[PDB]
Image (cartoon, rainbow, N blue to C red; front, side, top):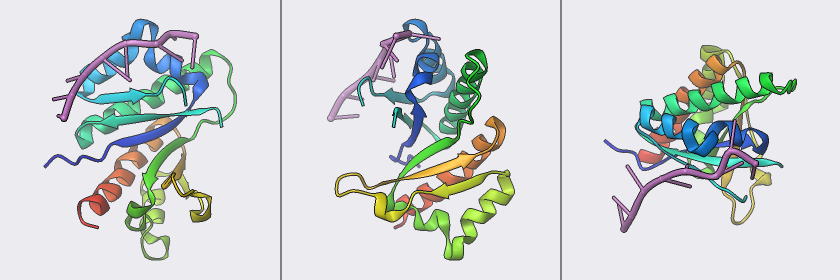
Length: 160
RNA sequence: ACGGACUC
């Protein structure tokens, strides 16, 4: 029933302060409301990883809160550039997400109204096996795409 | 730096 595989996001360092909040208040609320364990590295592109461990539903809820917080802060500081959702996933667990001929990926794109691209295999390194899944859309469409992407990642984890 | 946090 529990899947040990966390959701891992890549977010711009600029927005981590809003995610965590003064004295941890914001992230404290998220982890309480979504019953999740969320890890942000203090030192670590000017992007930082966030690891979210929870049920599928609590994981999607925490991701959606982080996307909402980040979009608000971008508006607050007149940050005009798009902020795609970026999911990290081990190379061993992406073939099911993509599917024969990209079929599964394109279906998620059409179902969620996002544009999803995966980093090229040859950008991996010996000791970084994580591909970057970039999801372009609104807060709402990106959150739905996260739900569908991680279903496929977990399906591969739990079988493959 | 709005850096919070629950083990194995």
